[PDB]
Amino acid sequence: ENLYFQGSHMVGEKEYKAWEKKLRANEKELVKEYTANAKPFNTYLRANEGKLGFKPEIDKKILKLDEALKKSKLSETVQVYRGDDTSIFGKEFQNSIYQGNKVNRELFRKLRDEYQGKIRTEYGYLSTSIVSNQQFAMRPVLTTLKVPKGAHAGYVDKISQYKGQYELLLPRNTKYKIDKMYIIVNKGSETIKIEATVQP
């Protein structure tokens, strides 16, 4: 263990290296493979609510990817984030929840009532961002996730010279409790905030 001068240069670099060490060569390539084209995997898991058996070749990779994600446990509780469009809320609210750069308060109240306090599931693998020096909240919806110590997760390197951070790749079938929803009033915009806790 070398001395960590300046602490972590970008948050998640330690966890990324450690996880990478435990992965077999075939696993590491499968992770890259998933990262390149995630959509066929995640639409499949969503279409069938996490049940396997429909597509044998896909099923085999999903099982291997699941095991790879098992290799690293979180040493400490962390916070990760997601930017999303109003499509996150589904047909009833997408088009309505906003009107001209501001949140519809009455529709927000209904939205808060349906989601807040409930436990939900992401059948696909969940990509989240780890804050280092910047948090990209340009999107209307910002979701913050508390990932508990002892949870399983993977790490993907999305970092470039000017933009990008480490990704925390959550296992498929992740459960989360929607702790709180509120409107962040920015200078010149409004953001819908979702604060959730990953149940392990």
Image (cartoon, rainbow, N blue to C red):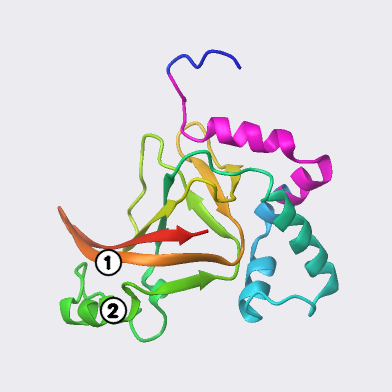
Give amino acid for label 1. Answer: Met
Q: Quadrant of the N terminus?
A: top right
The kind of secondary structure element at disc 2 is helix
The answer, for residue 61, to whether it is visible in the render is yes
Residue 163 rendering spot, x and y as whole percentages: 46, 39
Residue 7 horizontal side relative to residue 135, left or right: right
Pick whichever, 128 or 117, lies toward us. Answer: 117
Q: Which residue is mark 2?
A: 111
Mark closest to the chain's N terminus, 2 or 1: 2
Graded by Cα atoms within 10 Å as few (under 14), some (14 to 19) or many (20 or more), the crowding at tag 2 reads some
Residue sitting at 80 percent across and 41 percent down?
24
Q: Which residue is mark 1?
A: 181
Pick whichever, 126 or 189, lies toward us. Answer: 126
Residue sitting at 43 percent across and 72 percent down?
119
Residue 37 rendering spot, x and y as whole percentages: 68, 59
Residue sitting at 27 percent across and 75 percent down?
112
Residue 168 horizontal side relative to residue 178, left or right: right
The kind of secondary structure element at disc 1 is strand
Above or below, 92 relative to 112: below
Give amino acid for label 2. Answer: Leu
Q: How many numbered tags mark residues here?
A: 2
Residue 73 lies in magenta, yes or no? no
Pick whichever, 162 or 57, lies toward us. Answer: 57
Residue 43 rendering spot, x and y as whole percentages: 63, 73
Above or below, 16 relative to 4: below
Region rendered in magenta: 7-31
